[PDB]
Image (cartoon, rainbow over all chains, first blue to last red; front, side):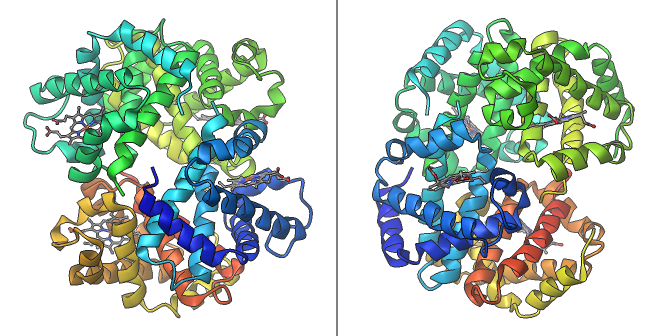
Length: 143
Length: 143
Length: 147
Length: 147
Ligand code: HEM
Ligand code: HEM
Ligand code: HEM
Ligand code: HEM
């Protein structure tokens, strides 16, 4: 569980990285598809081959980060605030939970890569705890 | 998260397997040490070499199952009802989270092995969800 | 890798009691039920939308038997498992892309099903031990290419 | 396994920019901080009870450098990684018993540290890709014996 401290740290980071989220999400998604090809199976409907340069991915990049920005805004109830993404992911698309870890990593990687001075050891801990909690909320509708 | 249905299923199973818990826990712990030797590193203080036949393990067997019986009794707040086991495990002993999965498996294995007719597919789902939730409560004090 | 006579014995002896067409279907069925995200891989099985759909679907029963035949291939070639699983690795991990951890999950479900069938007096800590070292190898041989 | 010139190039080129004594300490330090259950393995490092204890402890910095030297062993023997990691596998997985998934965690932390050091214009999707295929191999070569 996220502690109030954890929430406070995620809030300071997010406020700081916001706006740039769109490029961070394009990057994060773009890197997962390329570095962990097993994830591409969930995006085979998309066209040009999947990297940061394809439009679908760069647009879906801002999409994920928007949802993440929204999760931060409801950090006190990710479950309730994320039930529709969960029904979509866990129920409709049947995404393997094991992939949530992959996206998270690519996201933290992008953040540290963009705001290195601000992604200190303590922040890295909280943001990792938050992303882990996010996946938990999204895994809600599996079974 | 456990649904009320999930709780109802765990409750019916537990009431049914109770008493025999002591032998189930001896079995579960006894099997983890033997089948997944990486776990023995947490019990090197114990004597005779670790199997179901050693006293320490057979007694600690009833111990775990007692805590599990207690978790079932506070199924509505495993976090609050398990904070001391968490501080002990996650903070004091520094148990690797990855091992919670191992014990759970050996426990479900024992249950199905003892009450096969009662460990139907639907029960297996709930009891697995519960054990997963239990580990989550115990991982509370890690960071 | 290093198998002892005691290990080959326990494993062979256990595979020899097991009825593939009975444990297979049940195991593959549980995988789909207990861990529903695994359903995405068997879209060609038709109706598996509910647990009774699953438990009754003959395509699921058929495939469960194919899985047990795949395991027989290893029990038959215990010292070359990795090489004899050359095809199954590629399929599952280079073509289908089943996350590695799912191999472990099905490995666990089968063990559990093996357990509920024979009991604590045949599936002893000693057997359970040789058996687990066996599945750990299968699991490792099944994955790779994804990374 | 199958490394292309493009891959060897990107990897070699990246290992060649990296300052081991700087990324190593930071990486091993983060492992201990972010995933505190890993502390149980380094009980011989003395004071690492707090995050500043950790960040300042010279034994942690020293060991972080040993880890980067261990990685250099692979970048130097990219086509025999598994065999050259014969000792490190045994130590970590047969003697110490580090759960496999921790290898992945440190692999991720280093990548992240590599990322925060060089930026998106050196650590490009293309490099990031060759690099990840590299760590996936190291990780696989480091574990085994536990099962
Ligand atoms: C854990 C963090 C995740 C977040 C915050 C996230 C967020 C979202 C959002 C905001 C959407 C767009 C929904 C819509 O159009 O209604 C979506 C859709 C989707 N997500 Fe996720 N997602 C996450 C993880 C993943 C992962 C791990 C995968 C699998 C590799 C994935 C696969 C998909 C797919 C396939 C779609 C539908 C896309 C389309 O064709 O339009 N997502 N996700
Ligand atoms: C996830 C389910 C678990 C439950 C319900 C459980 C329960 C308990 C209980 C009831 C105790 C006895 C506490 C006391 O004496 O105050 C305990 C202690 C302990 N547990 Fe766990 N445990 C679990 C998992 C594990 C795992 C995964 C490991 C590691 C392989 C482990 C390692 C230990 C150790 C080393 C002790 C102290 C033992 C001694 O020397 O007396 N436990 N646990
Ligand atoms: C004990 C582990 C497993 C064994 C031994 C095993 C064995 C097999 C065998 C023997 C085949 C037939 C291969 C061929 O066409 O040559 C197969 C195919 C397949 N397996 Fe597995 N398997 C295992 C685990 C899994 C898991 C965990 C999943 C899913 C999450 C999976 C998904 C599939 C799929 C999707 C096919 C082909 C099906 C289709 O085209 O619809 N397998 N497996
Ligand atoms: C990128 C992955 C890793 C690499 C390349 C690596 C490399 C090394 C190297 C080069 C050594 C020195 C070996 C020797 O004595 O011959 C070592 C030792 C050690 N490593 Fe790792 N390691 C990795 C991950 C880990 C992880 C994740 C843990 C802990 C959770 C760990 C725990 C240890 C321990 C405990 C020692 C010996 C320390 C002592 O006796 O106090 N290593 N490692």
